[PDB]
Length: 137
Length: 100
Length: 100
Length: 100
Ligand SMILES: [Mg+2]
Image (cartoon, rainbow over all chains, first blue to last red; front, side, top):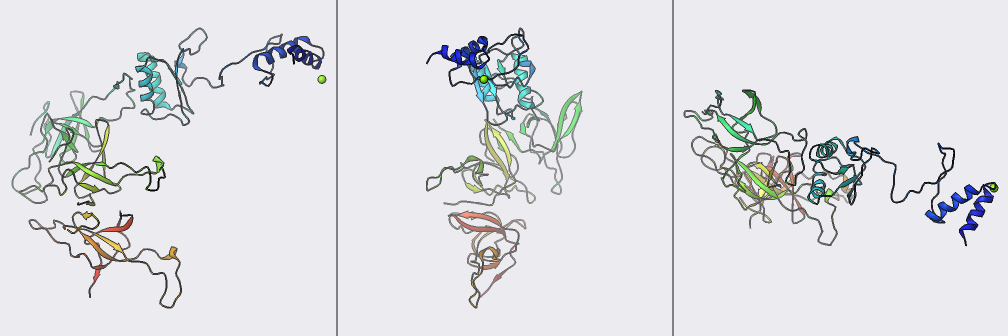
């Protein structure tokens, strides 16, 4: 009934290591008692706990030209429209109205799709590098 | 037959200039030039004297110079006049003229 | 010939618009749009002047504007007038018309 | 031409209805429906106005409505009138009529 008991159980089960017990108790405080906790190796001498909130998935860019924050080489928008496609966006006609909405409302657009082919990529990169449209695929 | 830039096509042959390909949509989205295809809207800049399908008189070309017309996909010949592109079609190959 | 939306077809070409594809049956079952195919029913919105089958006079088109016709499966040209799709056929390619 | 079910074919096109395929022999042996094929015997239910094979006058169609005819195995177009199947042929495609 207490997180101190959680820390005590994790400390006893880790051969009396109170740092492992404390870090498991902190992870279980943050993501919940029935949450997801994954162990992996570290490149640093000390153990560390990283909390990933929201919906983070391991898919990067499609075009490197979409970077609008050169400090971390990343794409950064706030209050952005999201266009989700179950199929790979291929035709130009399938991407022109979404860009028209995103430009008429003056709001960024994140296009999450199965893939984006060369024509739609060329339209997106041209509208980013020529007129300055806030888009990312 | 009408001659355009020292060029007069023979028989029922119509020389047209294709309209400029679109690059910016109505909402402000710029379009890539490579995915624009060929423009099917043209304007007639030269006409021939026509053909002899009926014996005796000569048949004038249905279109005239200064008419906007709709082109088919295939059937044109590229003519380079003063390093500018024009397209030669037949009189019967023209689909229809925009009237106003 | 009679023009439609500032477009007059040339010779014996006929511009029609396809009828709306069915989406719900008489029993009340909704249809998927990808299995609809191509609508063979149309109405004539523009006619041309016609061709010259014989010497002298010019032959008018058999159909007129406002006639419902049955189209063949193939033999039409897609014409985009103000971002709406119309189809250009020949006069002889029309299978028949519905009289009333 | 003579219309049928609000359908009048154009030019020298003949709309016919195929006869019912046989399912029982003269002795009493029933036939499977999947091996019947297409019936080459039909009856004329609609005729066109004919074709302009010669200049001036219009040529009537050789067959009239109510003639039993023999169809070639290729050359017909399927037409769905009142959810019933009919076939369009040319006037010259008809092989011969059964006279009585
Ligand atoms: Mg243990």
